Image 1 (tube, protein in one colour):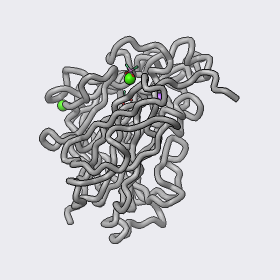
Image 2 (cartoon, rainbow, N blue to C red):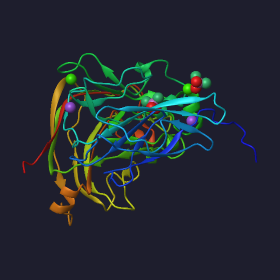
Image 3 (cartoon, helix red, strand yellow):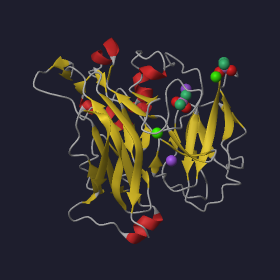
Image 4 (cartoon, protein in one colour):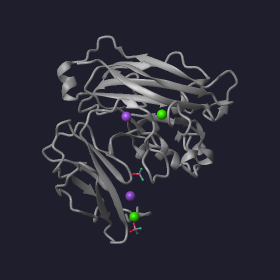
Amino acid sequence: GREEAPNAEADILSCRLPGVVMTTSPIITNNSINIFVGPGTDISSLAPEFTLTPGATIDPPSGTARDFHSPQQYTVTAADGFWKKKYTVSVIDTELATIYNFEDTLGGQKYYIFVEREGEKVVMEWASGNAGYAMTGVPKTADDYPTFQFANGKTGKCLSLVTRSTGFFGSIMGMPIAAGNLFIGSFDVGNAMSNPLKATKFGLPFRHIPTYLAGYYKYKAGDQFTEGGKPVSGKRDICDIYAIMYETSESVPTLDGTNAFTSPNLVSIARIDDAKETDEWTYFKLPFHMLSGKYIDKEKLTAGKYNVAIVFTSSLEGDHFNGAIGSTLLIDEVELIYRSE
Ligand SMILES: C[As](C)(=O)[O-]
Ligand SMILES: C[As](C)(=O)[O-]
Ligand SMILES: [Ca+2]
Ligand SMILES: [Ca+2]
Ligand code: NA
Ligand code: NA
């Protein structure tokens, strides 16, 4: 029958590049698309094609050739001619960034999105659950979210991850707390409050053999550990810091919160095993373990058939709502170290 609440604004629902192999699915947010192509692809004249909300139009039209050396804007107008939305569409044609100083974020947003740059060119957007937290109605400003930027880093600014209450609305959804996280991948806001573990899509293509994840942290557990909203006395919160490498396929384009450590597609895992509460910047250097009966194939590697994810969280079991509100993980000067070829 007739739609109950018409969604007003019209969306780009998909993106593809006819005749170019994308290295992973385009990452679509409310007002942005990131398209990934192999290093060496000519990006001076790409012609993205979109699907849209029925009855919408897009300007310039779907299939217009443009120069994506810089991001290009499109406007979608709803059928009614009143509602419009601007999207920024960017093409990433470089290999994954591996040096993270947490200085750079996207301006003009209601919460922080950390990016990696080469000069003025953005080459990666980190993801978090921020889009999901916005849906609880709790945050007022960028600093109220679980994932934000803090001025006092080890050098310059740093990443700050704080486990937050999700308030009344979060509790009625069975989601009473929100861990601060940051990861390589994307956040699918359509699952944020229906299948939250499916919302965190971990990994992007990586064409080297990672050997160590290194960097610095500080950590303070929150005062009162809770399990599904219920206080528990014997427990102190702890952070998690980890990285995974897995082989992609038609059936496994990404891993997520349901299978980050268990998917048979995993080839390698690095993970902190001596995390502690500390107010001093503490070095970690996590070796990647290649898993039993797995191997990194050279030709798959060069073809881009493996993804790597790096994940930080202020509450190790926060993804299952076990954690302490106020748990705070600061991260700075991280490096993904890989073998020289
Ligand atoms: C960061 As947005 C307004 O494209 O979801
Ligand atoms: C109705 As409008 C502000 O999306 O042009
Ligand atoms: Ca608008
Ligand atoms: Ca820094
Ligand atoms: Na919309
Ligand atoms: Na960087």
